[PDB]
Length: 177
Length: 171
Image (tube, rainbow over all chains, first blue to last red; front, side, top):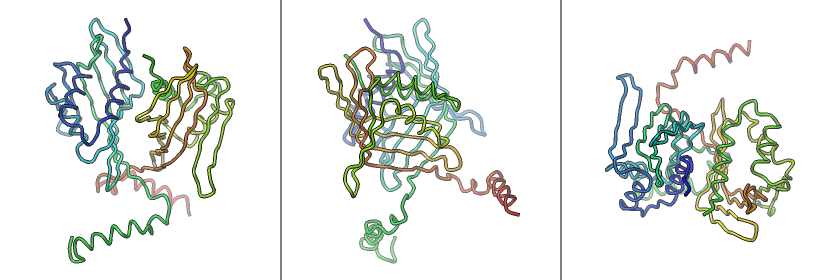
């Protein structure tokens, strides 16, 4: 009766990523993959290095493992910004071809780094009622680790920062790290 | 099954089509697309002296958004997290306690600025679904700088070139 256009599917995927928790198990990730990918889908990461092109292709089975992995090291947020996508409708598929795609991951402590991985993202959807990704190909061109700067001078005098210093010397020694 | 939060995704997409040469007329069409003819926009702070509220009238709403692009900014988008949607007579409320306004700067710092807080949006329950009120309570602010990832970046001859250009501007 209706049909989701493909950019709404991606907003859905960002929204679903936002409800992941530190308690989300592997079954939650399996359902994430079942929601958005096809049963035979693949996910490819591509780099152009001095040695030549580097392909990393993940089968459908490990697509859930991949997303769980991106979250592993204290990550709290992951989302996708697609800038100026081009859609092309085919007989049985739609392709979303984004030249400026940014994958954003927010880290927690101690750095609270915002990581931006940017490149070309090619998405092949099925012209389906379900509208799931059949191929995900991400060619990485650019990478940034953004660190919050200390905005005010008095921040370097915060007694909580100095306590963190003193709490190291309490648990470890002064001659000890 | 109507989905009001996506209206802001569309705003994000629409903002991306802004160019370095986007008119005042362009921003007036932007405002007309997403805001009612009588909308207001309010930013709020809780400060040492009490609530401070800044409210913009509809005619000043396009100039709000283009001002955000005046410092050499290249991107502006909104990230809404765990929004609660509410349906009234003729209105829908979108209340997001984790709204992030993200702006990308250009040279020399290439900063990414994240302004975060509570965003409340009142939409008309009609076919255009345009914003009646936009109320943003700013609770958190971060200026993120790209770090230098590799030690050899400090020896880059283009970095030394800009230094050399500087000393020329001295005598």
